Amino acid sequence: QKIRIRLKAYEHRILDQSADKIVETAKRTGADVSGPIPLPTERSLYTVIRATHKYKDSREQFEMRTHKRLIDIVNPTPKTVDALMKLDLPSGVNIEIKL
Amino acid sequence: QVQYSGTGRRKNAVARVRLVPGTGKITVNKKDVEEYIPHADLREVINQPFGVTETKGAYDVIVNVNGGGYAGQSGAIRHGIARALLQVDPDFRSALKRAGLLTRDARMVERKKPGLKKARKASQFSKR
Amino acid sequence: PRKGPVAKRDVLPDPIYNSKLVTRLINRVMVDGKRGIAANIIYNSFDIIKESTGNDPLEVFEQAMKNVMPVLEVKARRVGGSNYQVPVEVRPERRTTLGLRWVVNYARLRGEHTMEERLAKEIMDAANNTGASVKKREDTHKMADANRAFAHYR
Amino acid sequence: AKKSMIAKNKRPAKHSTQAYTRCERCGRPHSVYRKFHLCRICFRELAYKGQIPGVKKASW
Amino acid sequence: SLKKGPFVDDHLMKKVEAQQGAEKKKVIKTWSRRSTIFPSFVGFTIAVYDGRKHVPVYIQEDMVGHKLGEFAPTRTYR
Amino acid sequence: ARIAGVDIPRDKRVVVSLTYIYGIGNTTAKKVLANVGVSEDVRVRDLTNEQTDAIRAEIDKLKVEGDLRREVNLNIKRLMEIGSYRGIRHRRGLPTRGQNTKNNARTRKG
RNA sequence: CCAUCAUUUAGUUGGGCACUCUAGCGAGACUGCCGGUGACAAACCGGAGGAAGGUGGGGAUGACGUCAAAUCAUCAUGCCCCUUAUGACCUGGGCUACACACGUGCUACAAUGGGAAGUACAACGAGUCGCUAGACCGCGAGGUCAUGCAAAUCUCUUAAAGCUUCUCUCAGUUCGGAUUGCAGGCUGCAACUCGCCUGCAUGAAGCCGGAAUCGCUAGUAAUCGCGGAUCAGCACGCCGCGGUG
Ligand SMILES: [Zn+2]
């Protein structure tokens, strides 16, 4: 509703931590923030041969999960915009605010 | 009205079943169970809980099913119908319990391993 | 195996006739896991049995089974470098196993234009002490009760 | 010859269908992943040491 | 299947246009085995490099849609 | 005699018996029988002398005869007498399309 | 997502988070109770309850050592060798050659089948100069105008075996689809040597395979399709997924 967040990360611990940060500092100055809704956690898969020259019949498999989290804000106020676009922690987590 | 709801799972398929007093009939996904699963006789697998306990009518059955194949999502329907019958009267948890009809079948598709043709079939060998 | 004997693989009695024997017969006709085709075949065959000079498909089927199953089978063994064969008894499950196996194998080799025209005809010929299945049983009984010679002290 | 060929790989190609990928640490031309720009067995080497962010060993 | 106009090379077509006037020379020596035989190549004698040498091929009329490489093989069996 | 060239078989439907003339496959028989209006009806050739002449006059507009074998023959003949790489292979019993001859000539060379 | 309500082509729009689902945090399985065997011991056999019972099912995890096993061509590196050439740049040709022998696969030898019409049911994954909705043109592979989407929102994607009708009749055949002729499409500066696909025509061997030999103990074997890494294009190979069983 005319303001909403999106957060991607590789660790759900950091993800939930920052989601609680934003939810708390949002409902401190406003009201009615839709919960941190979870999204379905994309996954990839990489198979590789673990030997430099021969032996195709023995491999090692890797992956990279990407956790997702959604937060929608209802009825912002000329102070929520301020108190939201300023908090920034932590480092390796993607934030994308679309109106 | 009064109604009874249960949830049934089998082999990548999940069903949502509703028991309602009536005259004995079942419709699934807005079609008739004679047409939705018209295979041969899987219906006689579905109507087994009514056959063993709460013998045998009369409830119209309304189900919402999605996932798996035609033979998985009928064992799932059976699972759900049994759970719903259990909900009606708890005294049924013995006759049903004796004849299976209450457990989830945890027989899923085994995963493929590398270096093998399938989950367990290996390549052809030659001693020389 | 090596550890010791194993279980018996419980079967699920088919709902039409409520008979575990029809279940195993469906399982033996089936090839490649296409089970609905095998079921249609068995049911058309029983319809053909009852419609034409029949009483009930279970009755004539049981009698055909009784006339085909063996009661004395031999086993070719090795001792120390010379091999022979000796008769032995036959436990019950192996009996019905062999019966079903022979009936299906020798109906599959008939030479008509439908598996039903073969199966119904063959188990009718069997319930009247005829057909290569009964002759296979009698070959077995004749091999036994003769090769008891080098079996009398085995 | 593997020092002139890395040089020849980085100059602009003479035709559209003449460019090809190589590894960036080494110059291996076979089996390179084009999300990382790493070959078959530098991936397995930098996955250990936890340098590539994301990637880890999979089991299920 | 170049239904968007068949394919010659500029050097080859330049040379053939240049000789189009009078009676022709056997010295049209090009590598160019990808070019097709346009209906103006008739009567000349093209030299087609086969990876080792320059084989001459005389262009009759029945050869009018094929390529210049179809008349100079490369393998040398028996 | 029978309805084209020689000897369209008996006892079969026309949509299949018409296949037996060199140059008539399966869709061509359909199109020929449809430009007239003849069906199969049922598993026999019990036509009329108007149906035979009907399905006879239209085959004349195609190349279904020993007029086709001539075309194919003289095509391979033109091939092998210019250069020609395809014809050179036609003259050795070897695959003429690029086939990596390790087994793929048992058809082409027996 | 749609159970209690109105509404339309419809979960769509008003409404709701009940159910399914998604994903964080917890519970639950321990021979833990009950009977017998056994040196009363460890352990084994049977029962109750429960979704699950005896390491519930599967993965990752590979000791001291053996074969001077494999790799100076992923990368490094001691010693030796070349240096107006064993270094370097370009076009065209092999790497795809064919009297044959060996290994690993795919398609079949048909009626538990081939052909025509109708009706159904999944899961894992991929996408910005990419995935293409829809409408039209072409018998077809495809083409044109155009639309949504950086994605639980749009697309790839109506899965194939299956089921129901109508045929065909035991034949080298309405089985099989090798090989060859002609005409096209797509990517690419360019498909002769040497690509994939389409249509019409042709229609080979093959009627279940000796000695010998291989895989597999349950959602497994057998059978059926779908996705993506690599990649303009190019898969019967490889890695995964689910259906019938
Ligand atoms: Zn590398």
Image (cartoon, coloured by chain):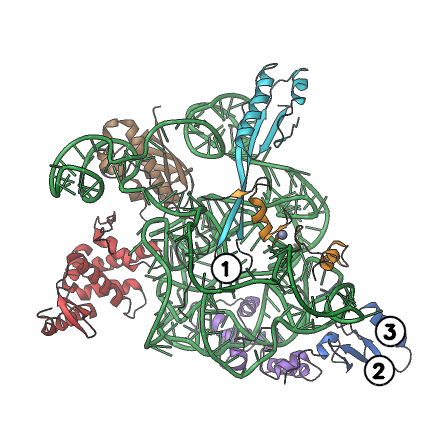
Chain colours: A cyan, B brown, C red, D orange, E blue, F purple, G green
Marks 2 and 3 close (CB-CB < 8 Å): no
- Of tags 1 and 3, the one toward the viewer is 1
D26, C112: nearer the viewer: D26
- Image coords of residue C145 (percent x, y): 10, 71
Circle 1 is placed at which residue position? Answer: A55
Chain letter of the residue beneath label 3 in the structure image: E
User: Could you tell me how far apart the alpha carbons at marks 2 and 1 are, in whole angstroms?
Assistant: 57 Å
User: What secondary structure is marked by label 3?
Assistant: helix
User: What secondary structure is marked by label 1?
Assistant: loop
G19, B59: nearer the viewer: G19
Residue type at mark 1? Tyr
Circle 2 is placed at which residue position? Answer: E26
In the rendered image of this protein, does residue E59 appear above or below residue B124?
below
Mark on residue E15? 3
User: Could you tell me how far apart the alpha carbons at marks 1 and 3 are, in whole angstroms?
Assistant: 56 Å
Q: In which quarter of the image is the N terminus of chain E?
A: bottom right
Q: Is residue G218 left or right of residue B113?
A: left
In the rendered image of this protein, does residue G231 appear above or below residue A91?
below
Chain letter of the residue beneath label 1 in the structure image: A
Q: Quadrant of the C terminus of chain E?
A: bottom right
Q: Image quarter for residue G184?
A: bottom right
Numbered circles on residues, count: 3
Residue type at mark 3? Lys
Residue type at mark 2? Lys
- Whether residue B22 is visible, yes or no, is no
User: What secondary structure is marked by label 2?
Assistant: loop
